[PDB]
Image (cartoon, rainbow, N blue to C red):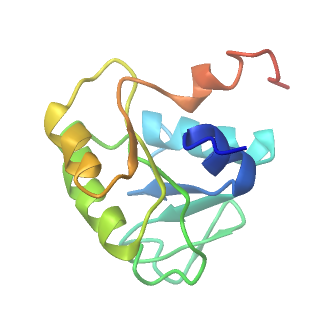
Amino acid sequence: MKENDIAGILTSTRTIALVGASDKPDRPSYRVMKYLLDQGYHVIPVSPKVAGKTLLGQQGYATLADVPEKVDMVDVFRNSEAAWGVAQEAIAIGAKTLWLQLGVINEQAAVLAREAGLSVVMDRCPAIELPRLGLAK
């Protein structure tokens, strides 16, 4: 099994990290958060406001460099350009996977990961990636 793709990273370690997890239930960043939590996945929301607080039962953090748990998949839904800033940071600490917002295309953030080898995935969301096979509860 010498497969070098997201399949091995997702099948090996499943870790989802949320960037900019605030108290805005009227945003796509929230709907995706509680969505991954209910589905039964490890959600690690990190925000400058949740730093030292509890979000939906998940420990909050001011920065991704403050959480002990190693992130495996960075969920960036905040904004388009946000993917770039969140990408460099992830690759810095030693990320493994990167997920952006579905419908958007960022060549800058895409290559920004290739430079390190990180698995960058743009124009794709977990909400639709889950049911893609039919394992949605």
Say whether residue 119 is left or right of residue 81: right
Q: Which residue is found at the position 48% from the left and 72% from the top?
A: 50
Q: Which residue is found at the position 29% from the left and 58% from the top?
A: 116
Q: Residue furthest front?
A: 2
Q: Look at the image and tell me whether residue 63 can be seen.
A: no
Q: Position of residue 9 (x, y in %)?
A: 62, 50
Q: Position of residue 95 (x, y in %)?
A: 44, 63
In the picture, the quarter occupied by the N terminus is top right
User: 95 or 117: nearer the eye?
Assistant: 117
Say whether residue 6 is left or right of residue 21: right
In the picture, the quarter occupied by the C terminus is top right
Q: Which residue is found at the position 14% from the left and 39% from the top?
A: 108
Query: What is the quadrant of residue 62 in the picture?
Result: bottom left
Q: Position of residue 112 (x, y in %)?
A: 20, 49
Say whether residue 70 is left or right of residue 85: right
Q: Look at the image and tell me whether residue 70 can be seen.
A: yes
Query: How many numbered badges does the structure rendering display?
Result: 0
Q: Position of residue 103 (x, y in %)?
A: 34, 17
User: 5 or 120: nearer the eye?
Assistant: 5
